[PDB]
Structure formats: C-alpha cells, structure tokens
Length: 31
Image (cartoon, rainbow, N blue to C red):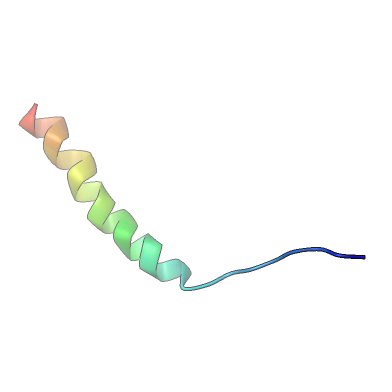
C-alpha cells in the first residue's frame, strides 16, 4: 500500500535553531 515519507536539510533548521535561540534569548532579556 501507499505510504509517505521525507527528510531534508535537517541541519539548516538546526542552524536556524541557533538563530531561533538568540531571539529565544533576546526578548527574554529585552523584556
């Protein structure tokens, strides 16, 4: 039968997770 899958460029969002982490941190101090 049918199924679905994917995976792509996981580090990019993981790199963005770093770039999220700053704005996870910044307004957490900018407040």
